[PDB]
Image (cartoon, rainbow, N blue to C red):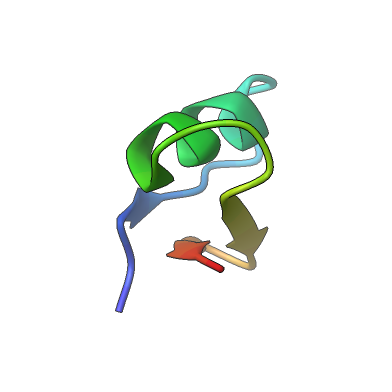
Length: 37
């Protein structure tokens, strides 16, 4: 399912997950998975 991981130790995890999913607001970190909304 995941675009990439979300690691809580990475304080920029939400910005990285958005980048994976195509831009601002497009990715959600849900536990350890970046999911493209």
